Length: 126
Length: 125
DNA sequence: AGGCTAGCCTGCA
DNA sequence: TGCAGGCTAGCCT
Ligand SMILES: [Cl-]
Ligand SMILES: [Zn+2]
Ligand SMILES: [Zn+2]
Image (cartoon, rainbow over all chains, first blue to last red; front, side):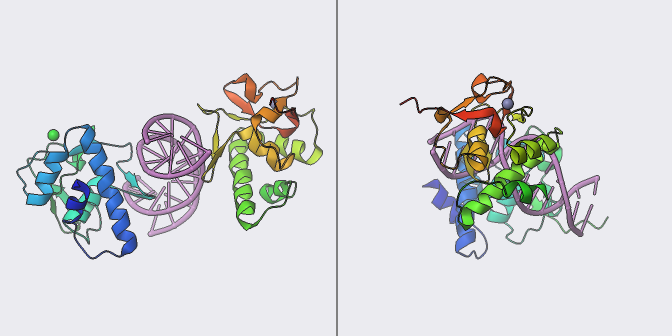
């Protein structure tokens, strides 16, 4: 199972409750990418940590947030926190790489959630 | 508070969990009627049991059901059970009065939830 | 019949 | 003004 494999790459120490939510977050993404033929691309990006992977996109919602098991957040933040930066505070601490065509900031119809298409930045000064 | 007053007219015996759900049902209806200026009419129908009150309408959903908290049901059944018949089992046991212009069965854009616009009927079975 | 969530509304910083 | 969280109609199983 792809879900369990992807969960093995999860960052940080999680308690019982967070482990269950994290599993739901991965399941939710796996369902969306399976219908658009983007699942293999997610496995490649996560399991190899490769920046030279395609955009991994999901439809953008009106307010940009994604709800998973009663929790709401920005999906690129959710998946960057899960697989790269467990203490990631907000979207203000993420900047997309130059080659990311569907970065969150672009506000296109689709949003890229490939964590290796983002870089962590210090909280903006101004 | 109109919620506490309308809840005083609630029928049946309720435990702690049902009491909280019933309060949510009344709150949910009060919110909807406040925006359409029909709250005073609900107070009138519930406190006077007058069949000669206007239709108390809420927008009709695609499947007819209403969700209050995490429970789904037919809204005229919900509010008829709350204020008139606590052992009302289904919509099949209810029929709208002749003067009800927005009866559930009519399937109009708006649905009447005035309990005094409905009567109990023999179960079709 | 019942579960999940995007959109809607709302109060807070 | 953005940000956060409650509620539920529409959609799905
Ligand atoms: Cl792509
Ligand atoms: Zn990208
Ligand atoms: Zn009526």
